[PDB]
Amino acid sequence: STYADYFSAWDKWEKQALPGEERDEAVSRLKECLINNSDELRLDRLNLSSLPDNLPAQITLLNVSYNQLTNLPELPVTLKKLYSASNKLSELPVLPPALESLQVQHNELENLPALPDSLLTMNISYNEIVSLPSLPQALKNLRATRNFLTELPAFVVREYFFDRNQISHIPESILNLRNECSIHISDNPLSSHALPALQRLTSSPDYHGPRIYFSMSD
Protein backbone atom coordinates (compact mmCIF):
# COMPACT_ATOMS: atom_id res chain seq x y z
CA SER A 1 0.00 0.00 0.00
CA THR A 2 1.31 3.44 -1.09
CA TYR A 3 0.91 6.74 0.78
CA ALA A 4 -1.68 7.91 -1.71
CA ASP A 5 -3.73 4.74 -1.13
CA TYR A 6 -3.65 5.18 2.66
CA PHE A 7 -4.48 8.88 2.71
CA SER A 8 -7.17 8.53 0.04
CA ALA A 9 -9.07 5.81 1.92
CA TRP A 10 -8.82 7.70 5.23
CA ASP A 11 -9.95 11.02 3.88
CA LYS A 12 -12.90 9.33 2.18
CA TRP A 13 -13.79 7.60 5.46
CA GLU A 14 -13.55 10.87 7.46
CA LYS A 15 -16.15 12.61 5.31
CA GLN A 16 -18.80 10.08 6.40
CA ALA A 17 -18.49 10.69 10.21
CA LEU A 18 -21.76 10.87 12.14
CA PRO A 19 -22.18 13.84 14.47
CA GLY A 20 -19.89 13.46 17.50
CA GLU A 21 -17.85 10.71 15.83
CA GLU A 22 -14.24 11.89 15.82
CA ARG A 23 -13.06 10.47 12.45
CA ASP A 24 -11.18 13.72 12.01
CA GLU A 25 -8.99 13.02 15.02
CA ALA A 26 -8.68 9.36 13.96
CA VAL A 27 -7.33 10.39 10.55
CA SER A 28 -4.79 12.77 12.17
CA ARG A 29 -3.54 9.91 14.35
CA LEU A 30 -3.45 7.48 11.42
CA LYS A 31 -1.40 10.05 9.42
CA GLU A 32 0.91 10.64 12.40
CA CYS A 33 1.41 6.88 12.66
CA LEU A 34 2.36 6.50 8.98
CA ILE A 35 4.58 9.65 8.84
CA ASN A 36 6.59 8.55 11.85
CA ASN A 37 6.52 4.84 11.01
CA SER A 38 5.23 4.23 14.55
CA ASP A 39 4.88 0.85 16.09
CA GLU A 40 1.72 1.92 17.97
CA LEU A 41 -1.66 3.19 16.84
CA ARG A 42 -4.19 4.41 19.44
CA LEU A 43 -7.70 5.28 18.25
CA ASP A 44 -9.30 4.72 21.67
CA ARG A 45 -12.20 6.92 22.87
CA LEU A 46 -13.11 8.54 19.52
CA ASN A 47 -16.80 7.47 19.36
CA LEU A 48 -15.93 5.48 16.23
CA SER A 49 -18.66 3.36 14.68
CA SER A 50 -16.19 1.88 12.19
CA LEU A 51 -12.50 1.97 11.21
CA PRO A 52 -11.11 2.66 7.69
CA ASP A 53 -10.31 -0.57 5.79
CA ASN A 54 -6.53 -0.17 5.62
CA LEU A 55 -4.58 0.29 8.88
CA PRO A 56 -0.83 1.11 8.72
CA ALA A 57 0.80 -2.20 8.01
CA GLN A 58 3.84 -1.80 10.23
CA ILE A 59 2.04 -1.55 13.58
CA THR A 60 2.73 -3.99 16.35
CA LEU A 61 0.08 -2.54 18.73
CA LEU A 62 -3.47 -1.46 17.88
CA ASN A 63 -5.70 0.04 20.58
CA VAL A 64 -9.24 0.75 19.41
CA SER A 65 -10.86 0.27 22.83
CA TYR A 66 -13.74 2.40 24.04
CA ASN A 67 -15.48 2.96 20.68
CA GLN A 68 -18.75 1.77 19.10
CA LEU A 69 -17.18 -0.65 16.60
CA THR A 70 -19.17 -3.60 15.31
CA ASN A 71 -16.42 -5.23 13.16
CA LEU A 72 -12.65 -4.93 12.90
CA PRO A 73 -11.00 -4.74 9.49
CA GLU A 74 -8.29 -7.20 8.54
CA LEU A 75 -5.45 -6.80 11.03
CA PRO A 76 -1.79 -6.19 10.23
CA VAL A 77 -0.06 -9.61 10.20
CA THR A 78 2.72 -7.91 12.29
CA LEU A 79 0.40 -7.24 15.18
CA LYS A 80 1.55 -8.32 18.65
CA LYS A 81 -1.03 -6.59 20.86
CA LEU A 82 -4.65 -6.01 20.09
CA TYR A 83 -6.74 -3.96 22.54
CA SER A 84 -10.36 -3.53 21.36
CA ALA A 85 -12.26 -3.71 24.65
CA SER A 86 -15.56 -1.88 25.19
CA ASN A 87 -16.92 -1.98 21.67
CA LYS A 88 -19.82 -3.92 20.11
CA LEU A 89 -17.87 -6.54 18.16
CA SER A 90 -19.98 -9.55 17.20
CA GLU A 91 -16.97 -11.51 15.98
CA LEU A 92 -13.22 -11.19 15.64
CA PRO A 93 -11.33 -11.56 12.39
CA VAL A 94 -8.68 -14.26 12.01
CA LEU A 95 -6.00 -13.23 14.49
CA PRO A 96 -2.52 -12.04 13.41
CA PRO A 97 -0.56 -15.19 13.67
CA ALA A 98 2.10 -14.02 16.13
CA LEU A 99 -0.28 -12.09 18.47
CA GLU A 100 0.86 -11.91 22.14
CA SER A 101 -1.96 -10.05 23.85
CA LEU A 102 -5.69 -10.01 23.16
CA GLN A 103 -7.89 -7.63 25.16
CA VAL A 104 -11.49 -7.83 23.91
CA GLN A 105 -13.51 -7.70 27.15
CA HIS A 106 -16.93 -5.94 26.92
CA ASN A 107 -18.04 -6.77 23.40
CA GLU A 108 -20.79 -8.99 22.00
CA LEU A 109 -18.61 -11.97 20.97
CA GLU A 110 -20.36 -15.32 20.61
CA ASN A 111 -17.36 -17.39 19.44
CA LEU A 112 -13.62 -16.92 19.27
CA PRO A 113 -11.26 -17.60 16.31
CA ALA A 114 -8.22 -19.87 16.60
CA LEU A 115 -5.78 -18.65 19.23
CA PRO A 116 -2.18 -18.20 18.04
CA ASP A 117 0.35 -20.23 19.95
CA SER A 118 2.21 -16.98 20.70
CA LEU A 119 -0.63 -15.67 22.94
CA LEU A 120 0.49 -14.84 26.51
CA THR A 121 -2.53 -13.04 27.88
CA MET A 122 -6.18 -12.77 26.90
CA ASN A 123 -9.16 -11.00 28.43
CA ILE A 124 -12.47 -12.08 26.86
CA SER A 125 -14.59 -11.14 29.87
CA TYR A 126 -18.08 -9.72 29.41
CA ASN A 127 -19.00 -11.39 26.15
CA GLU A 128 -21.42 -14.20 25.25
CA ILE A 129 -18.93 -16.97 24.51
CA VAL A 130 -20.24 -20.52 25.07
CA SER A 131 -17.06 -22.56 24.43
CA LEU A 132 -13.32 -22.10 24.06
CA PRO A 133 -11.06 -23.47 21.34
CA SER A 134 -7.65 -25.02 21.99
CA LEU A 135 -5.72 -22.83 24.44
CA PRO A 136 -2.12 -21.80 23.63
CA GLN A 137 0.62 -23.52 25.63
CA ALA A 138 2.19 -20.11 26.21
CA LEU A 139 -0.95 -18.77 27.83
CA LYS A 140 -0.25 -17.22 31.25
CA ASN A 141 -3.38 -15.22 31.96
CA LEU A 142 -6.95 -15.91 30.85
CA ARG A 143 -9.73 -13.62 32.07
CA ALA A 144 -13.14 -14.90 31.00
CA THR A 145 -15.44 -13.48 33.68
CA ARG A 146 -19.11 -13.12 32.72
CA ASN A 147 -19.32 -15.37 29.68
CA PHE A 148 -21.63 -18.34 29.16
CA LEU A 149 -19.20 -21.19 29.36
CA THR A 150 -20.67 -24.42 30.71
CA GLU A 151 -17.45 -26.33 31.33
CA LEU A 152 -13.92 -25.53 32.26
CA PRO A 153 -11.37 -26.08 29.44
CA ALA A 154 -9.38 -29.30 30.05
CA PHE A 155 -5.87 -27.84 30.60
CA VAL A 156 4.61 -20.26 34.86
CA VAL A 157 2.40 -18.52 37.45
CA ARG A 158 -0.99 -18.91 35.68
CA GLU A 159 -4.28 -17.27 36.57
CA TYR A 160 -7.60 -18.30 34.98
CA PHE A 161 -10.76 -16.27 35.72
CA PHE A 162 -14.10 -18.04 35.07
CA ASP A 163 -16.30 -16.22 37.63
CA ARG A 164 -19.92 -15.53 36.67
CA ASN A 165 -20.15 -18.16 33.90
CA GLN A 166 -22.59 -21.10 33.58
CA ILE A 167 -20.21 -23.78 34.89
CA SER A 168 -22.01 -26.51 36.77
CA HIS A 169 -19.30 -29.14 37.35
CA ILE A 170 -15.93 -28.98 39.00
CA PRO A 171 -13.81 -31.43 36.97
CA GLU A 172 -11.27 -33.69 38.55
CA SER A 173 -8.75 -32.11 36.13
CA ILE A 174 -8.81 -28.99 38.32
CA LEU A 175 -7.68 -30.91 41.39
CA ASN A 176 -4.51 -31.79 39.40
CA LEU A 177 -3.04 -28.30 38.83
CA ARG A 178 -0.17 -26.94 40.98
CA ASN A 179 -0.17 -24.27 43.73
CA GLU A 180 1.25 -21.82 41.16
CA CYS A 181 -2.09 -21.95 39.30
CA SER A 182 -5.01 -19.83 40.50
CA ILE A 183 -8.54 -20.66 39.23
CA HIS A 184 -11.48 -18.37 39.91
CA ILE A 185 -14.79 -20.00 39.69
CA SER A 186 -17.02 -17.86 41.99
CA ASP A 187 -20.67 -17.24 41.19
CA ASN A 188 -21.31 -20.21 38.86
CA PRO A 189 -24.28 -22.58 39.17
CA LEU A 190 -22.22 -25.26 40.91
CA SER A 191 -23.75 -27.85 43.24
CA SER A 192 -24.57 -26.26 46.57
CA HIS A 193 -22.26 -28.94 47.98
CA ALA A 194 -19.33 -27.47 46.12
CA LEU A 195 -18.69 -24.54 48.50
CA PRO A 196 -18.46 -26.46 51.79
CA ALA A 197 -16.54 -29.25 50.13
CA LEU A 198 -14.06 -26.89 48.50
CA GLN A 199 -13.79 -24.86 51.70
CA ARG A 200 -12.69 -27.94 53.68
CA LEU A 201 -10.42 -29.30 50.92
CA THR A 202 -8.47 -26.10 50.30
CA SER A 203 -8.30 -24.98 53.94
CA SER A 204 -6.58 -28.11 55.23
CA PRO A 205 -2.92 -27.81 56.27
CA ASP A 206 -1.98 -30.66 53.92
CA TYR A 207 -3.85 -29.38 50.83
CA HIS A 208 -1.82 -29.70 47.63
CA GLY A 209 -3.59 -28.27 44.59
CA PRO A 210 -4.33 -25.06 42.69
CA ARG A 211 -5.41 -21.94 44.55
CA ILE A 212 -9.18 -22.03 43.88
CA TYR A 213 -11.44 -19.03 44.52
CA PHE A 214 -15.02 -20.23 44.69
CA SER A 215 -17.29 -18.22 46.98
CA MET A 216 -18.93 -14.76 47.02
CA SER A 217 -16.72 -14.68 50.13
CA ASP A 218 -19.16 -17.03 52.00
Image (cartoon, helix red, strand yellow):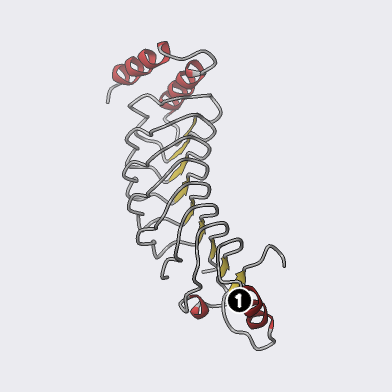
Position of the C terminus by quadrant: bottom right
Instruction: Determine whether 143 is above or below 83 in the image.
Output: below
Nearest the viewer among 167 and 191 is 191
Using a 10 Å C-alpha cutoff, classify the residue at mark 1 as few (fewer than 14 neighbours), some (14 to 19) or many (20 or more). Answer: few
Left or right of residue 70: residue 20 = right
Residue indicated by mark 1 = 193
Mark 1 lies on a secondary structure that is loop
Residue found farthest to the front: 192
Nearest the viewer among 33 and 188 is 188
Instruction: Determine whether 148 is above or below 196 in the image.
Output: above
What's the residue type where badge 1 is placed? His
The residue drawn where x is 46% and y is 48% is 128
Please state the horizontal and vertical placement of residue 7, each as a whole percent of the image. Answer: 35, 17
Residue found farthest to the left: 1
Please state the horizontal and vertical placement of residue 167, each as a whole percent of the image. Answer: 50, 64
Please state the horizontal and vertical placement of residue 175, each as a whole percent of the image. Answer: 52, 79
Position of the N terminus by quadrant: top left
Residue found farthest to the top: 15
The residue drawn where x is 47% and y is 79% is 172
Query: Exactly how many numbered labels are in the figure?
Result: 1
The residue drawn where x is 48% and y is 23% is 29
Nearest the viewer among 80 and 176 is 176
Instruction: Determine whether 52 is above or below 12 in the image.
Output: below
Please state the horizontal and vertical placement of residue 129, each as a whole percent of the image. Answer: 43, 51
The residue drawn where x is 48% and y is 50% is 124
Instruction: Determine whether 93 is above or below 175 in the image.
Output: above
Dividing the picture into quadrants, the one containing residue 157 is: bottom right
Left or right of residue 55: residue 107 = right
Dividing the picture into quadrants, the one containing residue 159 is: bottom right
Residue found farthest to the right: 218
